[PDB]
Image (cartoon, rainbow over all chains, first blue to last red; front, side):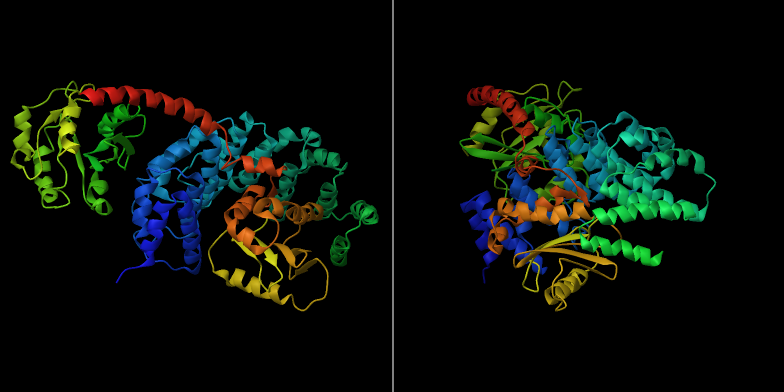
Length: 290
Length: 159
Length: 165
């Protein structure tokens, strides 16, 4: 009549965490199949709200994440609210990495009854001086925006003002990515502002705007000058990325004989400079289109 | 030992707890869930579930239906409200058998906080007067008071 | 995102490990991909192939392939750095090379994907430093000693209160 589920249970005792680790791996593999039959849940439940083992928690957590959670128990196993309060604390945790890590997870996470006061909780965490933590919120939020955008409704602006408060490029970059997805307009307003400053700045964020601008014109234009003013500055162009895009965007925008020429040059030099052949071909392909 | 703090926690039922644990107070949202601490004595380390007796959480505790070893009832001694009603619930604990494996303490908390009943008055009222197949000495705390508690407890692990 | 999955590959027709940024489907997207990869399509050499607007990006590193996939345009170099970069990282991450070591440090490795790359963004430099961020921290400790201690005092004191009363 008895089973090795139990066999694992003693091991855990035996080691502690260590044995459990082993158990996680096994479980994992077991999990990996799909497969498992419940009961260890209880164990897990028992020891884990009163236990640390951070790594293990990380394993555990992730396991929860990858695995379902709207589990035939509910929805939730049904404790998805209670346990969380420790976790919420952790999420609260003064302990910034710890929160950040959670957040990382959290971006992956999407479990609602738990979320609601964690909405409050998160808000606090944004304030924490760590850009890692804050950045993590940007993903997380992104995750909300599809899942329950509304959950938070005032956000697009809130962000946008936030940007104002902000200055970490990494976070900014992110900020843009999400911001346009929420609404371009805010980005644009800012865009107006930024126009001169751009040149000074780091690429990655710059890139993101290039996509956005594209979609809108085919639908409707009349907008140019303000852009142009900048755009000309962009006709410096110099990173291999920048250049790669820069001619590419241009064509998207224009095809005047003068335009034709501008881009063309960029290529030709580029090529000449160019080394990865794979690359070379690619531009051709564009060219082939052209 | 598994020691149980039930009733709706957020009232400072949890305060009662936080006061033990750090010395502090409810600096949490009023807390439905398991709150866990281990307290070590006789080095039985008492694992305390301070759990709100709020709706689900009261409703659902079956995995925690296992076998008890210690009883705190943390009390709003201003509550003198849900207790009869409680008595009415409480029977089903009585009707549990896991529940008869603990020599316990009801703790009257929240005394300063408004008032409290006759130690007796309560005793019938939750239905408490009636036990014996578990010990049943009585101990008042408050939640800004409580001492000699430990006498209560002393007997209790050493039952 | 700029990558819905990173899968690290071994020659076997099979990719040694993988992670699914986003779940929905089943492996058949991933499963199918795995199959195709194993097959290689007999194709001779070339470290890149994109077909049908899907980049299949790989790097043989030995008998191993590290693979990334994408469909719409990218700036190459960056990318390369990564493949290569992977090829810098592993003996540190999971220990050297042989599946097993990795098999033990799976968690570490997956963690590295996330860590390294937040949705197709090159997050940092410095591997050790990368360790640092979590399961290697600092704050928590600072807090703990003081706090734990404080509580402990209350507890100690409590021990007396308890003890006598």
